[PDB]
Image (cartoon, rainbow, N blue to C red; front, side):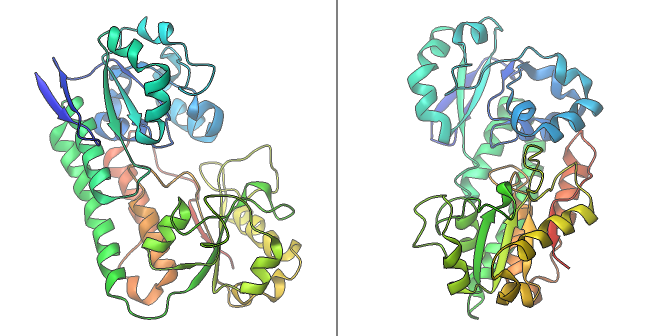
Length: 349
C-alpha cells in the first residue's frame, strides 16, 4: 500500500503502483512530461487514457513524440475537464487507477467529475507546476514518482530541477544592481497585432519578476491581456522578449519548438521590430536587447531552463556559468524518451 501526499496536503493511498493513468493537460502542467521522464520507454505501459491537449494545442510535439513512440497514438482518447468533451462514464469505463489534476484545474474537476471518480474508486492526486514555487514543483515530482513506483528517479529529477532553480533564485536575491525594465509579449498574433502581456505576478510576468526584472506592465495589466502600443514607446524598456510557439494558423507568429529553424525564427522576431510603428527607434531594438523564449516551457517539470534563461538574459555577466539551452537539452537527454531538437530560445541578431 503506497501513501502519497499531494501538493495540497491530501493523503492518497494506492494498493500498488499506478499503471492505468488518465492524463489531463498534457504538455501544459499536467503529468505527461513528468510521467515520460519517470517511465522513459515504458511510458505507454502506465497510461489508460490520453487527453487531446498535445494533439490540439501542441501538434508539433504530438508529431515528434508519436513518431518516436507510436504506441501513444493507440491509447484510448479522453475528453478534457472543463470542456464539453469530458465524459465521466467514458473515463470510468477505462478502469483507471489514478488521475493527476493540476491545482489550476482542481475547482472545475471537483465540480464536474470528482464525485464520479470517487464513486468508481479512482484516486485523485493534485499537482501544481503553475505556482512556480520550488516546494510545489518538488512535491509534484515526488507525488507522481511515488504513485508510479519510481521514487528514486523522481529524486533525480527533483534534484536536477532544484540545483538549477536555487542557483538562479539565490544569486538574483544577492544582485543589488538596478533591475532591467522588460516588456513581455506572447507573439501569437505576429507583428501586426499585439499579443497578451503580463502583470508582475502572473505567468511570464511572475517568472520575470522572480528572475530580477522590472516588468513595465506590472501595474497596467491585471493578469494577461494586451497592452496599448503607445505604452511600450513611452516606457522604452531595456529589454523586450516575444514568446514563440507552434501557431500554424498564424503565419507571422513568432515560431519556436520542434518545427522551427534558426533563420526563420530570426526573421520572425526581426519582423516584430521592423513592422511596428516606432519600434526601430526603441532602446531595446537599437541595443539588440530583443529575445524570445518558448511559451510552452513554463509551468512544467523542465521549466528550470526558463528560470535560467530569464536570469541570464537580465543579468548576462552574473550568469556566464549557466546555459539554459544546455539545461533543456540535458533534461531531454537524461530523462525523456523523446529526442531533443528544434529551437527554444532566441536572441535577435
